[PDB]
Image (tube, rainbow over all chains, first blue to last red; front, side, top):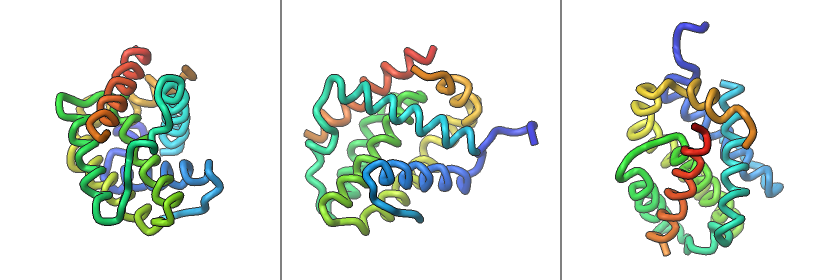
Length: 151
Length: 21
């Protein structure tokens, strides 16, 4: 099975989102559930992103102000600005990290049902707005090739 | 705060992009 891109369908992106969120929550000891080198590379890339981010900025959750009524709009506003002038793998990693932060903060703030919603919002945004860019730019395979190496 | 958050995500994202290449 080497003729086509790894994780080349929306169903695969969904799995990718669910595994990512499960991991981000597990790092905080919160248990939740709803391509293998792809999941591994994204874990690594997001962790390395977070490390760099935190060197320069305060905790990402310090500027969120989550409520159940405003969470979807907060998500959409942030992500729409993130990709307003374009897409690249670094911004896609930023997208996963932001979604993970939304989920962690939801559980922290005793709004844990929002996790399931955030996972759906991420999956939909990925499939509606990032997936065709991903296919046009070498698939998750290209991402693995570029971000596979540490740092 | 939301605008600033997005900008922080975007630039850190762009940095990462550039380092990979």
